[PDB]
RNA sequence: GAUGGGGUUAGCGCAAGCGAAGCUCUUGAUCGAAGCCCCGGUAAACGGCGGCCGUAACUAUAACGGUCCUAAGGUAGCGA
């Protein structure tokens, strides 16, 4: 099962190259309560 | 042609010599323009239009950066 290498024709280091493409992104939690937190409509919504 | 330095000298002295005046060879003081230097301009005047090193999500490149040098570092376009 392939991954479409955003980098393409990988010549030198495969690991490093991959780590520098969308597959190993910087992933950020959308936490509640604080900063970058507010949701207009919740997961289940207002009742 | 300023001065200075001679040079033979009417001579005077008993004489080494001083060497009147004048004569006269020099010395170039001063006077003294253009140009040159110098200041600015001009490249459709003649001409000239850089190096070295480092750098970005594999690699590669380097928009970018450091530095040195220049009068300035080749712009548009074009380009084995
Ligand atoms: Mg050919």
Image (cartoon, helix red, strand yellow):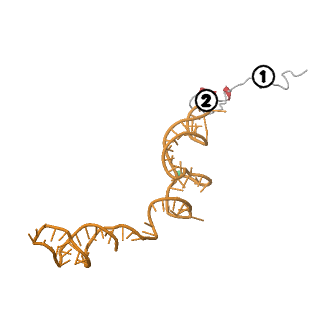
Residue B4 rendering spot, x and y as whole percentages: 28, 67
| Front position among marks 1 and 2 | 1
For the point 68% across and 26% down, which residue is it? A26
As helix, strand or loop, the secondary structure at mark 1 comes to: loop
Q: Observer-nearest residue: B15 or B67? A: B15
Crowdedness near tag 2: few (<14), some (14–19) or many (≥20) residues, C-alpha within 10 Å: some
Image: A39 above or below B33: above
Label 1 marks which chain's residue?
Answer: A
- Residue most extreme to the right: A47
Q: Percent x, y for residue A18?
A: 63, 28
Q: On the image, which quarter does residue A12 sit in?
A: top right
Name above or below for residue B15 compared with residue B77: below
The yes-or-no answer for disc 1 within 8 Å of ligand 1 is no
Q: Is residue B27 left or right of residue B80?
A: left
Q: Give the labeled residue for mark 2.
A: A17
Alpha-carbon neighbours of circle 1 within 10 Å: few (<14), some, or many (≥20)? Answer: few
Q: Quadrant of residue B24?
A: bottom left
Which quadrant of the figure contains the C terminus of chain A? Answer: top right
| Above or below for A43 versus B71 | above
Q: B67 and B2: which one is in front?
A: B2
User: Nearest the camera: B4 or A29?
Assistant: B4
**Tally of numbered discs:** 2
Please give left or right for residue A32 compared with residue B12 in the image.
Answer: right
Which residue is depicted at the point 60% across and 26% down?
A15
Q: Residue A39, how many percent across, how many down? A: 82, 25
Q: Which image quarter holds the N terminus of chain A? A: top right
Q: Which subunit holds the residue at mark 2?
A: A
Q: Can you give x and y, in whole percent of width and height, for residue B46 in the image? A: 50, 63
- First in sequence: mark 1 or mark 2? 2
Give the residue pinned by disc 1. Answer: A34
């Amino acid at each position: 099962s392939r991954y479409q290498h955003t980098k393409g024709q990988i010549k030198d280091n495969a690991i490093e190259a991959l780590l520098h493409d969308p597959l190993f992104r910087q992933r950020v939690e959308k936490n509640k309560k604080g900063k970058g937190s507010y949701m207009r409509k919740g997961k289940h919504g207002n009742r």
